[PDB]
Image (cartoon, rainbow, N blue to C red):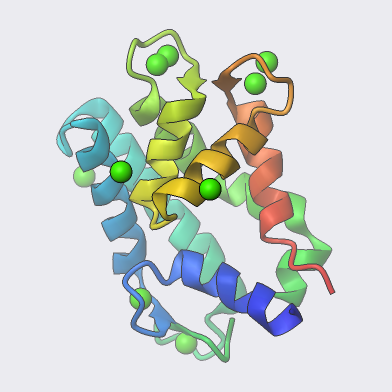
Length: 162
Ligand SMILES: [Ca+2]
Ligand SMILES: [Ca+2]
Ligand SMILES: [Ca+2]
Ligand SMILES: [Ca+2]
Ligand SMILES: [Ca+2]
Ligand SMILES: [Ca+2]
Ligand SMILES: [Ca+2]
Ligand SMILES: [Ca+2]
Ligand SMILES: [Ca+2]
């Protein structure tokens, strides 16, 4: 179970599935989300999402790329994330904020549960599970998913329970 839980988290970052985490895993994730919502890469929201993704890669690399080759292997990839999950969530905050912007289709600063599910599928979550996860992210049940729900959820998700 534990090792399976760890692989799940690794697989989330290893978007292209090739067994190491690269900047391009993150670039690819940004590209997928923008495509899902028809947001132009060159738009303000597009540039903000790529900048946020690049910042999260650098944070994660800072933590886990022990030999400095700018790929994080399965091997290199948990304890550091478990002991300080809040710090890692803040590293991800610009990315998560930008992702919400992209998934906000009417511009009112809120994202629907259905569009949260769309975002998750852009990041490789199969459609059925994404609906279930999106629903779970809406912890106050108002049908709107926000930064105050997503950022702590992210912190928790990357705290692999022992
Ligand atoms: Ca990869
Ligand atoms: Ca750019
Ligand atoms: Ca490395
Ligand atoms: Ca919306
Ligand atoms: Ca909205
Ligand atoms: Ca479908
Ligand atoms: Ca189902
Ligand atoms: Ca909510
Ligand atoms: Ca709410």
